[PDB]
Image 1: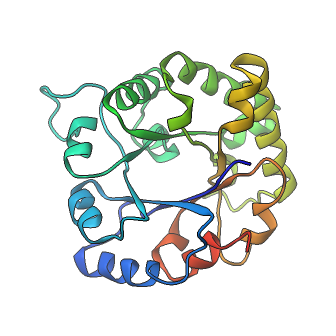
Image 2: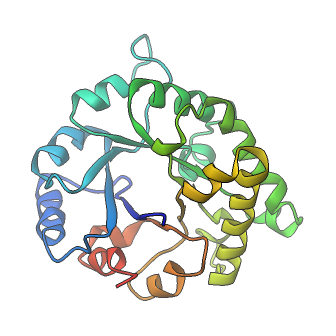
Length: 245
């Protein structure tokens, strides 16, 4: 029922020639039942949209919470739309933990981006001490609670769960562990927003996703796709797009 969604977050990787190389393999045989979005660096929104085929969406990796103003180094949803792009990733764990973006700011960004006409990939997830304290649910539910007041159109939202406790820590997140969080998030949507929203909203997994593990994760029950990191930079990404095939 929920359309499989695969986002490729290039992070701070790429130049014109490397992006041409990614586009080249993304013209390959992509599953027609998968919604595909790439998240390019801030300075390549126009270049990526210009040369990426129209069946692939393009996301900015961040934006601010108003259309214009005295915010040197920021870009707005209006600019992202002006660049021809439709999506933005918000609240990625690197923004939260390397650059200190708090929940209220991420929520306000989500609200402004939706009002401006973008589709949004809000990212949530718990750290290692939060998980080992048995606070996984407390944290991700509170992160969801922070976003809900600013989600004006659930049809334009795809939630990404990042197991931050397993990213960069050498620890392994198993498919059952990922599935358990996704199921609890969907139930939270059921109980706190609506059953209709819980059943139609994609919740994608943003742990370490590779050609080697994508098939294990793609059909656990409540995983609706992936927010892929480094594997989105190489032809392996096509295999991940085709994880249900």
